[PDB]
Image (cartoon, coloured by chain):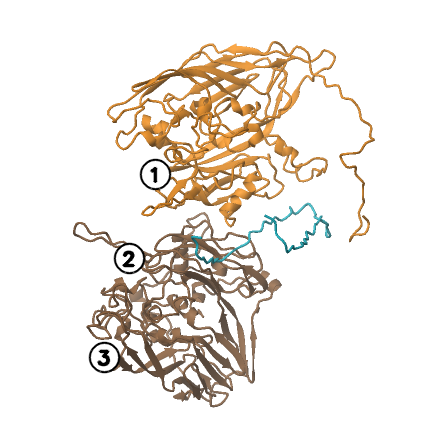
Chain colours: A brown, B orange, C cyan
């Protein structure tokens, strides 16, 4: 031990098979007396918007943070006149299924309110980039399984067909023990014949929010509130729920599917309530972590395709408080791909591949500027990117045998760089993830178009997330951001007691 | 006009037409008696070495800063098989001339020793990025007119063809009071026929390098020397003098001209020793400003074309002091042009368009990253760039009017950035334009090939000019750099009695 | 004429401002004054033509 320049202190550790002996204790695990579940059929609901209001039985009854709502529906497709031909049915065995996640990508904006105070997530645009981010294979296969789950990898559906992994495929043709393709989900068909299709079944989808959690790691439950209400509203077109492929749709013509129509019944949220046992009392007022996520977006009308890069810059934006992290990406632009049935159904959700980033921050310019794009990936994976370096970084070639074919290139989605703010930006002294007040940052970066078939007009987002504390008391809901005072942060004590990677589990 | 905001003083001034009253002296301009022009014929010259040894007649003689060599020459070219080809004469009315500037573009290194202290500069590479950069129109028709001087504005000679700005045109074809094409520079031809061409003339060229000058205005000469000299060593290939247009050759000739053998006859330099009037004395030991060119070129093999975009970097290179100015540009790499007679003659010396430049000053990164490539121009023309924005970033579109025909694009010879180092980088303090030492920089810029016809391996250059003072006395030649303490600079008084524009005049 | 008609359309557009922050030691005065010129124009029309 004291063989080095500085004697370092020794300890011995018993190898696992011979771990015995050490004092062992019998451990008794105590849950609350009564644990219950009830459906709340939405008190008011219609075509374009529906909502619930579901008061807890009493204060003094903790509630399960893991929530979800189940929605029964009806879709019927009509056969479009007059794309030429039309032989083979209207639905295909490998060519179409629900977009994932089906009822989340519809939702314009979720909105809950805890205890008289409002908390809200804009849900539609946000979910597709957030969802990439924290799932491993255990989690993607747990709760996250309920809605159709398989994110879209192929930059353009048509050429995907028919790979083992094709985003939309049936249950057969998925590998044993791994994320199953979107076509596996059960929807009974009342009738599928060329000219017409009608299909009908229930579909589940969680409330993605904070406090409420979607990932498994359990955490303490919301007590002690009095009122709870949820609100939802649907982003207009709503044909978008469905997905499709180009292969079936025909030369210099139109797709066969357009147009369809949808219909719902009354959907019902599902809340749990555990009422704690008489031995241990729950504290008068209590405090919960609470993160709120925004989005700031930019449109630039010009176009590039199939593969030539240019620069785009995002209008300078202000923040009220250093957010705990922020994602950056570019993607196909929302203003287009909303008009036209074909355009709505069959265009996948994916990202142009980032060639290099160069953000600035209050004011500076440029942080992260001189790092290979490669380098953005491997510092994002550190926060849990979970997709192979090749899935990120766009396209992959492919050669064929036979003279003389051309060698087909495939686009397959570009990554989304994410940087924690202490972890990767570096803040000037005595600013830390909570601290208020005023900052502004404008990312600017370059991106190359990946796919071969269409011209992509683009847009870019920036999703910032703010982390603070919220005090559900009886009865109020003071919510605080800027919990750490600036002077305060300077001279805070450093504990080696709590390891860092431990604080990577808290999420939100 | 003590009515505005905070009040201020008013002075009245006189219109030019009438002053008319003011104490008007008469200034007798005296310059020393017995001005003389010497003509030293080089002794010891070969095809590879010019070697003048030229002493001043006394101490007390003050020789003038503008020096220049003249050199008679003899070239012969002989047609190649198998072309072919060929009908026509070997030299063409538009196709050829000398490369500006003939004498320098061949010199490996010019070298001179003021008073036993060796001062040299490398002429071959540095000079073509030096030409573009400090001459307006007025100066281009002044002294610099003696060697061919018109700059290479087309990306490849073949495209310029017959055009009004075409570099290699006759005397006709260049408007009045305008820079002449290099074909107009006189030479007399013993024979020009198919198979053979034999030409002869006289070439001037001004000795470049400090403390001599090729600027028009001039300052005070270098009394009081006892020694002087000059030595040019030349590249052995020496075919680089001529320039030829690709149009004639066709495919697989590939070209008519090669080979060719150049020859020199003893050259002779011209110095001008004035001597001051007895009455007015010159000081015993006297001081002058003195700059010093330094270059590092970095080559990376990879080849982009005809018009791909890429990125590069240079190995870090430490410096011993802040340099007054700094020049960055991507050239068509040298190594590829040297092999072969065909190639050496028929490739103009031009630069690739800079899409964006980002560089790092010492241990500091991201500088200039955010600024638009058009912005690079804005602050560099302010330095004195003298060339239409259109030619910087060069590429131009001329469309033809006849059905079944595509329009054609023309490569235009990109630019070369330069950033005075206290002006355009900004400096942490106290640091100046001279202070030692040890800062380390590296550059990483993204370029685009614009040349329409050839794949181009590129290369990067960085020229700096360190600043200091050279003090000559008989008999010594002390030279310094640093010159001011890092503390003494921190508190020297800013004087309003000069115009920053005064320091633009002392090139440099 | 040959044309006809035409339509124009702009994409995102962007200003480019220079800045620089005066070196900490030297102090720029609190209140400063610059020259400024207001350019204004008027015109008068005429009914009869010449040619």
**Residue drawn at x 63%, y 37% as measured from the top left:** B486
Which residue bears the numbered disc 3? A192
Mark nearest the camera among 1 and 3 is 1
Write down the residue under mark 1: B453
- Label 1 and label 2: CA atoms lie apart by 29 Å
The quarter holding residue B107 reads: top left
Counting the numbered discs, the total is 3
> SS class of the residue under badge 2?
loop
Residue, x 34% and y 31% (percent of image)? B246
Judging depth in this view, the residue of A355 and A435 nearest the camera is A355
Query: Which corner quadrant of the image does residue B414 belong to?
Result: top left
From this view, report whether residue A397 is shown above or below residue A332: above
Q: Is residue B92 left or right of residue B114?
A: left
- Displayed quadrant of residue A245: bottom left
Horizontally, residue B70 falls left or right of residue B250, namely: right
Q: Counting residues from the N terminus, which is met first, the one under dot 3 or under dot 2?
A: 3
Res B190 visible? yes
Q: Which one is nearer the viewer's eye here, A493 or A289?
A: A289
Q: For the residues labelled 3 and 2, say whether their Cβ atoms are less than 8 Å apart.
A: no
In front: label 1 or label 2: 1
Mark 3 element type: strand
The answer to whether marks 1 and 2 sit on the same chain is no
**What's the chain of the residue with tag 1?**
B
Residue picked out by circle 2: A410
Asked whether disc 1 touches disc 2, contact meaning CB atoms under 8 Å apart, the reply is no
Task: Look at the numbered discs 1 and 3 and tell me whether their residues touch, using CB distance below 8 Å.
Answer: no
């Amino acid at each position: 031990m004291s063989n080095s320049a500085i004697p370092l202190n020794v300890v011995a550790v018993q190898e696992p098979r011979l771990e015995l002996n050490n004092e062992r204790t019998w451990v008794v695990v105590k849950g609350g007396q009564q644990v219950t579940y009830y459906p709340f059929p939405s008190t008011s609901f219609s075509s374009n918007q529906f909502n619930f209001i579901c008061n807890p039985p009493s204060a003094q009854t903790v509630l399960d943070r893991l929530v979800f709502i189940q929605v029964p529906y009806d879709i019927t497709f009509t056969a479009n006149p007059s794309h030429a031909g039309i032989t083979e049915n209207l639905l295909q065995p490998g060519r179409d299924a629900f977009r994932a996640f089906p009822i989340s990508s519809i939702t314009n904006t979720l909105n809950a309110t805890i205890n008289g105070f409002p908390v809200n997530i804009e849900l539609a645009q946000i979910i597709h980039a957030l969802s990439r981010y924290h799932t491993p294979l255990k989690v993607k296969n747990g709760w996250m399984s309920m809605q159709p789950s398989f994110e879209d990898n192929y930059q353009s559906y048509r050429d995907a067909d028919g790979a083992n992994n094709n985003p939309l495929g049936v249950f057969t043709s998925a590998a044993g023990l791994s994320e199953l393709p979107r076509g596996s989900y059960t929807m009974n068909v009342v009738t599928n014949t060329t000219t017409t299709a009608r299909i009908t079944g229930v579909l589940y989808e969680q409330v993605f929010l904070p406090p409420f959690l979607w990932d498994g790691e359990q955490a303490g439950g919301l007590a002690n509130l009095t009122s709870l209400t949820f609100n939802w509203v649907l982003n207009n077109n709503l044909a978008r729920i469905w997905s499709h492929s180009d292969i079936t749709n025909d030369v210099s013509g139109n797709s066969t599917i357009g147009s369809m129509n949808i219909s719902f019944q009354q959907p019902s949220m599902y809340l749990g309530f555990v009422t704690p046992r008489l031995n241990i009392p729950i504290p008068p007022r209590i405090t919960y972590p609470y993160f709120k996520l925004s989005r700031y977006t930019t449109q630039f009308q010009n176009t590039l395709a199939p593969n030539a890069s240019s620069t785009f810059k995002s209008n300078v934006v202000q923040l009220d408080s250093i957010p705990r992290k922020l994602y950056l990406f570019v993607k196909q632009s929302d203003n287009v791909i909303y008009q036209n049935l074909n355009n709505q159904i069959t265009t996948p959700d994916v990202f142009l591949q980032i060639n290099n980033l160069n953000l600035t921050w209050n004011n500076q310019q440029g942080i992260l500027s001189g790092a290979s794009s490669q380098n953005l990936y491997d510092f994002s994976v550190q926060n849990g990117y979970n997709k192979t370096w090749s899935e990120f970084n766009g396209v992959t070639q492919q050669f064929n045998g036979v003279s003389g074919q051309p060698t087909k290139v495939i686009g397959l989605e570009g990554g989304i760089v994410c940087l924690e703010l202490g972890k990767d930006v570096g803040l000037r002294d005595d600013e830390a993830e909570g601290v208020i007040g005023n900052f502004n940052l404008q990312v600017q970066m370059t991106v190359t178009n990946t796919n071969q078939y269409v011209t992509v007009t683009p847009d870019m987002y920036i999703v910032a997330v703010y982390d603070g504390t919220l005090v559900i008391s009886n009865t109020s809901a003071m919510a605080s951001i800027g919990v750490a005072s600036k002077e305060e942060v300077l001279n805070a004590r450093i504990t080696h007691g709590v390891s860092y990677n431990e604080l990577q589990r808290i999420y939100g």
